[PDB]
Length: 318
Ligand SMILES: *[C@@H]1O[C@H](CO)[C@@H](O[C@@H]2O[C@H](CO)[C@@H](O[C@H]3O[C@H](CO)[C@@H](O)[C@H](O)[C@@H]3O)[C@H](O)[C@H]2NC(C)=O)[C@H](O)[C@H]1NC(C)=O
Image 1 (spheres, rainbow, N blue to C red):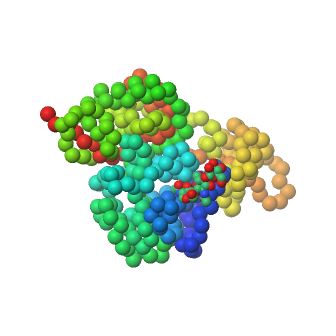
Image 2: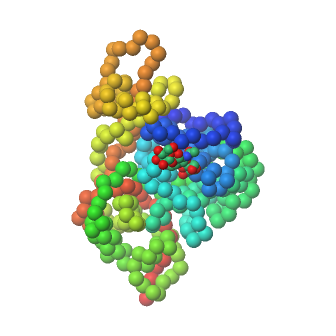
Image 3: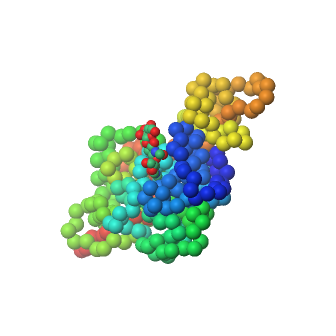
């Protein structure tokens, strides 16, 4: 949990405010408030996901998940809440991967080749074991549901990118195709030219989102987590209260008057020994290995999202 403990909602009726503060959105991300809001607008779902458990107790496919152990490594959905990308509503043509335990799940999200698709359920519903249907569920009637009903597939890390010229991305695009000549179409998105294809098959591939019209999938590739101590590397909470507001957090990150930990004070400035009563804002280093930088096709890329997920990939016929 980056900031806020597992949410304990009393109501399904409660509205989900949109908060401007970085920490505020991190807090909602912590309490899976963003999935709950994804569910409300798209599945006409009633209430919340992540009850008592929050984002840490979300279920991943696979369960043995690296980046999960790092609370500030952003999933596609957190990234969506942070506006970095958008997890699009499930359309009929987006393919549900086999593998995960979808039954019970009210929400599961998957990186497609072209983006990120969510499959949500209506109130009092939950996915069957296949994931292709929301069947009725008495366990979901309360509308305030546990985190293991949310499923994030893929070991995904999302992060502020360094944009790359399109010529660079086209180099990477074709480098992948020379690495993956076998594949013809991924998530309904044409990868190569084949004419003779086989029907969609699963595909465990590492990949990165470079901010372009699709991801680049990588067989061989090097990564190097580097620490940046940028302001997004810190969240700002009020002790006992929750996250600082939009202005309070900006003040801590610009002026250098709020309290913090070892690295936050080194970087943004803080003061110690003041007080008089009533405790202050504080900021702390988000826990993550850093910003991933990926060596691939001779290019050092700092991507929007890096992950190893399962997509569906059609193959050729010889
Ligand atoms: C579910 O529906 C919500 C309503 O559309 C939506 O929340 C809305 O999110 C957008 C995008 O973040 C916000 O848009 C604008 O907000 C401020 C001004 O208020 C601007 O500064 C921004 O630049 C942006 O243009 C809406 O304010 C916000 N509305 C409400 C009532 O919360 C959610 O995003 C939807 N759910 C998901 C998962 O996307």
